[PDB]
Length: 11
Length: 92
Image (cartoon, rainbow over all chains, first blue to last red):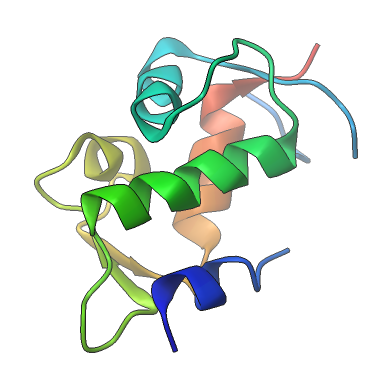
């Protein structure tokens, strides 16, 4: 997974 | 400093605002989700994420490190970020 995929997956 | 962090407008103190501006912000007033937006832009643009293990952000010789007060964090352990935000946002 890419950082931006992981980032937008945030509360 | 805030205790608990939709649509509510925040004004970031100067240290945080600098980082948001570098990230591309054209604004003095933000929503929380606009802050998180630009914060993620900043890590992207600056390439602070570890390139093999991209949930890890190395922020140690960077103005963001100074704000968070850690050398690294995990996107899956986002506490340093939320805690920095209540330290750095004025909630009107």
